[PDB]
Image (cartoon, each protein chain N blue to C red):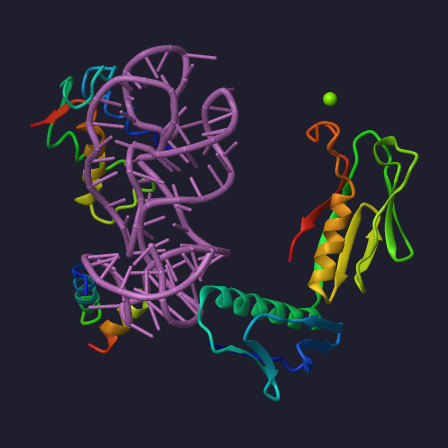
Length: 70
Length: 29
Length: 172
RNA sequence: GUCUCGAGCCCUAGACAGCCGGGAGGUGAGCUUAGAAGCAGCUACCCUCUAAGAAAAGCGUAACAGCUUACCGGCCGAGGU
Ligand SMILES: [Mg+2]
């Protein structure tokens, strides 16, 4: 029912494309409050118990695209 | 005795106080 | 070295010279086990394969004799089963058992019937498209099963187009 | 083929092999692209659950799927490499 994480980052960032080279080329930007809201949405999709460890999985897609957290 | 076996035997004792042969070695303790 | 084999309750094995005869509820398998300085015996109800020598050549046979005895035990208890399925593409092949020999007719369109022979006691029974080779002596069964597949050997043409013939489906 | 000898490393906290079981999710990585979802190509190769499980090693598919391989567990029981 709930759409994927790859389609949830492009809504609260600005850009719709990735990059020619991941990690090295920094395109999009997120924040502290901009990650704890994407964690409020996914529950049957994630295997994590805590609300702390659930955040670590969203980041596991971001640094491999070109996103810097402030 | 490899290091990983000892770190595991002690980690099983951490969930007893609070492989099948690695459970047995944690039971006798 | 020495290897002691426990003979089951359904099984009874007797010795006469170098010959071993294994009797049970499925039949009687007689075999001749011979090799230098190896002696096989029956200690009442255990089979003992022992030799004073421990060289690799001797260890090869002590091992082979064990599997020849262990497999003779299964022969007299449960028995040996090899399953075969007849396959044909264009020609209506007929596989009928006639006497102490299994016969195949009209193979690839031939007027001449291809006939093999049943080795020993072995029972080859057909249930339409299937065939099941069964018996106590694995030596006779595995060979009678082979003889059937091998009877449809075609070396003259490409086997990838001409795939007709009985094949082995189930190996025990 | 077989015999004798030495050396390093693994092993009853159960090795080697074999057979069984498991082989998970975020997630079809992203870009490339109508498409590529372990496995065309470029670059990265990151973290959850757990006893394990690769940004996938080998095959396989137009692509999925399927089969395994790393990796964990069980059976077994003695030396193994
Ligand atoms: Mg020709």
